Image (cartoon, rainbow, N blue to C red; front, side, top):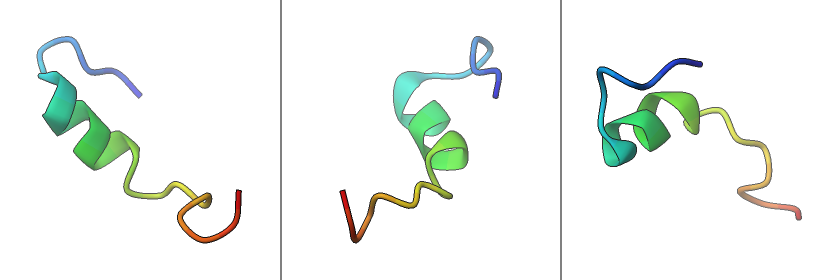
Amino acid sequence: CSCTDMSDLECMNFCHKDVIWVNRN
């Protein structure tokens, strides 16, 4: 995951769209 030519929100979008803790944490 490389977001440097990319903002924070946009990074969270593509890089955190597969986070598993969106139900259990």
